[PDB]
Image (cartoon, rainbow over all chains, first blue to last red; front, side):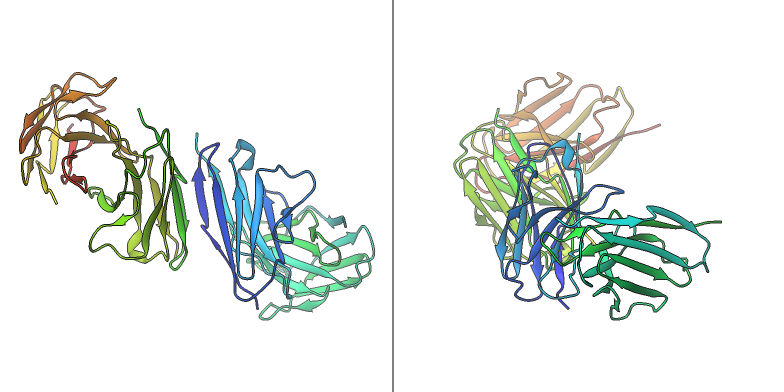
Length: 108
Length: 108
Length: 108
Length: 108
């Protein structure tokens, strides 16, 4: 359908680091991308929608960009609370496919 | 902001057993409900879209029904391999929202 | 002295992915940065010197940039041979300090 | 391209023992030799620079000598914690090059 390739699949970094996650769509999805945060045992939580629109009450350290086939999710300055798996989801054409996830770990 | 309520939050079924999980919408979403299967350590996989339409290559023991606000998801005979967390997601109104998920487990 | 902060400290990706590694220097180092590749049990091998100069016989998929305090190492398209730990080293002021390394793993 | 030859490639010493590793330069590098300690899973750490100058906070059982092309690195009494791979690096001529390293181990 529309394939979302997400990289890296895992990353470990330290607090205050910049974290960049990408998503490449199989075809032009314009800016129909959701970025979700999923803490363990939780349900994916909308961070960014419309590829670059931050959901109300989401720290400004999270940002997204791109259009077309290449999207970027940036965590400006990793904070101890950010441990989780991040996902991109295209909502352009059904089925609304998800990239593979990026497991973010924070080193002591 | 459509809230999606899902139950039960956890289950423990013996393989062979039938499973029904529901999603109640905080409003009329017609039939725009995605049902996902999230395996442990993997990304959410589309099982059903359009509330009842099965995805290509999805086992038929999986069925979806509902229209409006109430939706049901059924696994006809829990397989050893159905163990995962299932989620409903609304695609009516932006931003797309998920229900809390249901953690389906197998007993011994 | 001069502190090189490198992120991420670990990453796992797939073949054909773009990989971006950064190094932030404590102070202006101009373009006095070495990027090394270290396969297990091996000695660090110079990939890039002068921050952006590729060492003779190094695949063009490896590139580097930046000046001042922010340097980037990019692997254009990860290849199965690239499994290793990557390091930045500043050679501006003694002692010639190393960033913390990025362990690159490739998922099947 | 200065080649740096280092020996031995491996050692196995009993704690208390004295250790000498050398680095022969493929040419005259005066005294620009770095000696690094690379612990298992960590980045290279500067022990000696300027061939013989000890780094701030470095144990004195570590000494460096040589000028020209031949350099020696000595650990006066191998500590349980000296287990690592040591490396010499020339900083005379670009690009900076490392010797093959010496994997110092402790016996039982």
